Image (cartoon, coloured by chain):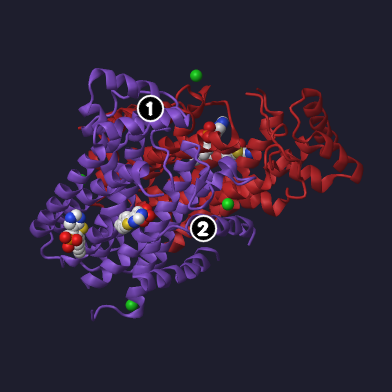
Chain colours: A red, B purple
Amino acid sequence: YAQEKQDFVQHFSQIVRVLTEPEIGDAIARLKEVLEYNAIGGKYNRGLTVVVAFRELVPRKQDADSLQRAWTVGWCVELLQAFFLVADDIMDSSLTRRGQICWYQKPGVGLDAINDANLLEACIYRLLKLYCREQPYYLNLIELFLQSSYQTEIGQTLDLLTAPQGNVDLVRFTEKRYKSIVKYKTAFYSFYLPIAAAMYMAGIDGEKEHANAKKILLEMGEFFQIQDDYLDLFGDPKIGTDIQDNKCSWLVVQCLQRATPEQYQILKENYGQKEAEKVARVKALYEELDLPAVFLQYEEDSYSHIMALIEQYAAPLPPAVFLGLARKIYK
Amino acid sequence: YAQEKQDFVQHFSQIVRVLTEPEIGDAIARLKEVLEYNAIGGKYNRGLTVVVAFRELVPRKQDADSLQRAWTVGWCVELLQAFFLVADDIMDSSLTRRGQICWYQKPGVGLDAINDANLLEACIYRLLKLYCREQPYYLNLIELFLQSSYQTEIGQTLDLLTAPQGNVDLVRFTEKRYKSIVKYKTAFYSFYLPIAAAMYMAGIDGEKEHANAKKILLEMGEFFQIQDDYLDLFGDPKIGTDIQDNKCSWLVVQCLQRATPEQYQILKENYGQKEAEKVARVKALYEELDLPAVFLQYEEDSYSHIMALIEQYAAPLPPAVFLGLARKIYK
Ligand SMILES: Cc1ccc(-c2sc3ncncc3c2CP(=O)(O)O)cc1
Ligand SMILES: Cc1ccc(-c2sc3ncncc3c2CP(=O)(O)O)cc1
Ligand SMILES: Cc1ccc(-c2sc3ncncc3c2CP(=O)(O)O)cc1
Ligand SMILES: Cc1ccc(-c2sc3ncncc3c2CP(=O)(O)O)cc1
Ligand SMILES: [Cl-]
Ligand SMILES: [Cl-]
Ligand SMILES: [Cl-]
Ligand SMILES: [Cl-]
């Protein structure tokens, strides 16, 4: 798996070579700089998942070119990721990303990052064309990536309406709403997309199979994010900033369901300010509501429920496809 | 033509209806607001051109559904336009657009406009799917719109490298470069895209025919922009701001080819400042170099050359497809 990871990373150089072949040379040079800064330095889990799932699904239809297409579509997933991140960082006014200055914050990039991010998106379909245009699943993959982009965008919109950074409102933060943001903004592209892509590459194109896989994978994405929000605040540290940013965090959502009217007010006064004594006091209200424990409870039920989902909906894909993801997430 | 224009506009309401069908309802409401503010209020020439060209190309394969698909793909062109404009306005820090406050400048939109613009792009492929997924040209159209987006982005990058607003450099402003910016940023999507789309809808999918049409239409896009840059400064007024913004304008490009070293300096000191006496003095240097006259000369040659292009490359499409565009532009 750490070995697969370095093969996946080593293939990047070729991705960049093929995307970067007279007077537009300067544009293409800037494209290369954008690729290199923004598509590298994550953990590569989403793109890798394409490759791993592709191997588990397919073994005597794995010639070097099949493999090369799998690495490439994995790279397409990472590019879609990069597009989202560069754009989200600008929208959120973030400072850092992946251990570096966010791209838009580099001197001389600024809002030109909007176009750079568009270029990252565009690169997905260039690669798909270059490597997959002859394949029976080509159109299936173009449509998967487009639908993933739309779901992710539509979730981002929902998020932005829900949690405007700099304006405290908690009547927006409902369970139904939290779950809707996670599904659209995060789970579809992070969980469904990579396995779905691998399924199509493997010839598995049926609506029912895809719907079966989606059921499991969206539910995994919900836990993954819920765990993310818990760890943001209670992890062993990268200290998080979710309460400082008026996020629609699973933590705050539970808080609000579980709170007396006096506690509602303690949240009103401290959710969103930058002051560490103000951040200290929501955290302590979360501890007073035993939210680490509700999470622990939540993690157990969620795990049971996922395995029931896999039991029920995995067939006829190898359960291992799902289990390896469950393994990674439920760590 | 003004009648066709109002039918085209009246179809918008339906476009919006079909794009705007539980908890993501709020996102979809915001999507509607984005569509309504940003896809309306232009002249609709690019989208209309799809419809007009579709009628000229196809008459006993024009059932109500064929027509509805043509209006829709026209709308897809306008959406691609809207995506570009909303994003470009943010990148350029523009104030107004189409007689209104630019979307990003509306209170409470701000940089959330980045996602709204992504949503406009996404809507293109939703409509294509909704209306064209069964058609033989479906994939041809998805790929056309993707390639148009890429060309436009790659040209925008070239522009942004060439003309960084707030930093005077004129060694960048070369003929070869000007022409490269116009082709990628403007001509492909403005001229090739709508006719190309109409060609595919009509069954005309050959690489040679498309390459023939492209030759004419890219050359029209070059003139159209060159005329734009001339009129920006010398039009009968919407007063333009190109010299105030250090644009790589056809005017400045000619100036620089035609200038003594002393005049180079007069340009160094006045290209880009906001001061109307400073803007007054480039304008007057353009008049002193008889650039209105070089343009007039340029417009005549360009017109001859286009008609030679149509003569040579139109067949077997009806020359009228091109001529109506030439008519509109050479007004
Ligand atoms: C498809 C998929 C696979 C793995 C992840 C994980 S496992 C993990 N462990 C510690 N920290 C983060 C993660 C992630 C999320 P990330 O790949 O770093 O965005 C997320 C999605
Ligand atoms: C392949 C695989 C997937 C998931 C597990 C996990 S994660 C978890 N979290 C809370 N409780 C139980 C589990 C399990 C089953 P375990 O008791 O570690 O073998 C173990 C192995
Ligand atoms: C395909 C196409 C058709 C028409 C245009 C024209 S004609 C005209 N006349 C005055 N002012 C502008 C124009 C345009 C450009 P625009 O449709 O307003 O962006 C541009 C492109
Ligand atoms: C269909 C049609 C297309 C173009 C023309 C134009 S635009 C132009 N600009 C400079 N010189 C000539 C032209 C012509 C030919 P014209 O002499 O107006 O009939 C006239 C009709
Ligand atoms: Cl092969
Ligand atoms: Cl850094
Ligand atoms: Cl029909
Ligand atoms: Cl207004």
Give me the chain letter of mark 2.
B
Residue in the image at 48% along x and 23% along y: A106
The answer to which quarter of the image holds residue A90 is: top right
User: Which is more toward the observer, B246 or B270?
Assistant: B270
Residue marked by disc 1: B271
Q: Amino acid at mark 1?
A: Tyr
Q: Nearer the viewer, residue B82 or B306?
A: B306
Which residue appears at 61% of the width and 41% of the height? A225
Q: Position of residue A167 (x, y in %)?
A: 73, 40
Q: Position of residue A218 (x, y in %)?
A: 55, 50
Q: Which residue is located at x 31 percent, y 80 percent?
A: B63
* Residue closest to the eye, B262 or A114: B262
Quarter-wise, where is residue B311 in the image?
bottom left
Residue furthest to the left: B312
Q: Residues within 10 Å of mark 2 (few under 14, many from 20)?
A: many
Quadrant occupied by the N terminus of chain B = bottom left
In the rendered structure, find residue A243 and report the number of the disc placed on it: none
Residue at 63% x, 36% y is: A228
Let me know if residue A256 appears in the view: yes
Vertical placement of B322 versus A144: above or below? below
**B105 with respect to B267 (left or right):** right
Q: Does residue A48 appear anywhere in the picture?
A: no
SS state under label 2: helix
Amino acid type, mark 2: Leu
At which x and y percent is residue A193?
45, 48
The kind of secondary structure element at disc 1 is loop
| On screen, residue B77 above or below B264 | below
Q: Chain of mark 1?
A: B
Q: Which residue is mark 2?
A: B35
- Badge 1 crowding class, 10 Å Cα cut-off, few under 14, some 14 to 19, many 20 or more, is many
